[PDB]
Amino acid sequence: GVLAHLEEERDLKITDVIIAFQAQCRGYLARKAFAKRQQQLTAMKVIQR
Amino acid sequence: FSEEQTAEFKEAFQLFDRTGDGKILYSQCGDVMRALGQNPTNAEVMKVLGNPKSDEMNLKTLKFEQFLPMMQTIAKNKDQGCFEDYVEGLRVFDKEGNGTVMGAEIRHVLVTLGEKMTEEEVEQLVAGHEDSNGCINYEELVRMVLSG
Amino acid sequence: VAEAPGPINFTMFLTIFGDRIAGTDEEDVIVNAFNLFDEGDGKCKEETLKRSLTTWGEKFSQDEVDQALSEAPIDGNGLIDIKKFAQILTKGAKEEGA
């Protein structure tokens, strides 16, 4: 058994890899991409007038 | 928060609305938290949301005085992931140790592990940061998501 | 004439003319009207301009759309918005004021 558990652990501590990174990726993406749905709105109001 | 920035925080929430009806959903909540200054784990959000499924996640509404305790509860937030953790986090698949990984594995791992991404979420994030061999160096990709 | 108190001469004329700074939206804002809805450099799918004018926010009648629709330059199932904007408000018509 022995050596194989240490390998197990070392995969287990890396099998998620990595929510905290993806959350930063996400974080970044929303506050940029939103600019579109931000943009189109008052434009729709011009169209109405 | 100060009524100074809280005024601004309110505005960005109001600019998230769809109609005017004052009600940003349990969905969009995550983007409002982001856009104010956060990068929550989708879990951090789910925590203060009160654990809904897709149905009432889409159906339940929020208003700002339902949101501001949420944004406040996270913000003074536990542990914020440094450059050093993150590089080792991506370093995981460097078959030897090189500092470099192929942009195909990297496009994929983010579409299979942790808070899984779509191709859309990945391509915009990663593209143009592979080199002339199709390796993305991770070290700069990590810095890129930091100062962004 | 009664948009001024009486003797609309060379000065009273321009006295009301300049001071009135408000009315309709600017044409470049009016390009932004549908130019901010497009997801790339492209156009606007006609289904989306019909569905919106009737359903969304401030609503038209059928009548209101059909009038706007015979005037509306449809091509390739896409109401290429940039031209319709110039169609409504460029060096526009005379006469109506002063």
Image: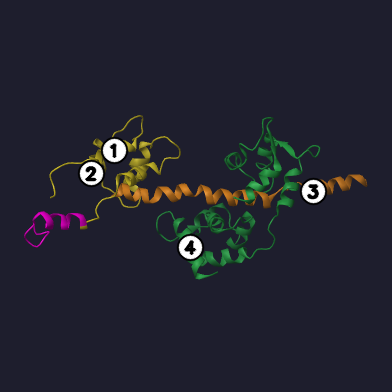
Q: Is residue B48 left or right of residue A35?
A: right
Q: Are marks 4 and 1 on the same chain?
A: no
Q: Which chain is orange?
A: A
Q: Is residue A12 left or right of residue B52?
A: right
Secondary structure type for disc 1: helix
Q: Nearer the viewer, residue A37 or B27?
A: A37
Q: In the image, which residues are magenta?
A: C1-18
Label 1 marks a residue whose chain is C
Q: Are marks 2 and 3 on the same chain?
A: no
Q: Which residue is mark 3?
A: A12
Q: Which residue is mark 2?
A: C63
Label 3 marks a residue whose chain is A
Q: Which residue is mark 1?
A: C84
Secondary structure type for disc 4: helix
Mark 2 or 1, closer to the camera: 1
Question: Can I make out residue A10 in this image?
Answer: yes
Q: Disc 3 marks which amino acid?
A: Leu
Mark 3–mark 1 contact, CB under 8 Å?
Answer: no
Q: Are marks 3 and 4 on the same chain?
A: no
Label drawn at residue B8:
4
State the image quarter where residue B14 is shown. Answer: bottom left
Q: Residues within 10 Å of mark 3 (few under 14, many from 20)?
A: few
- Distance, label 2 to label 1, CA atoms, is 18 Å
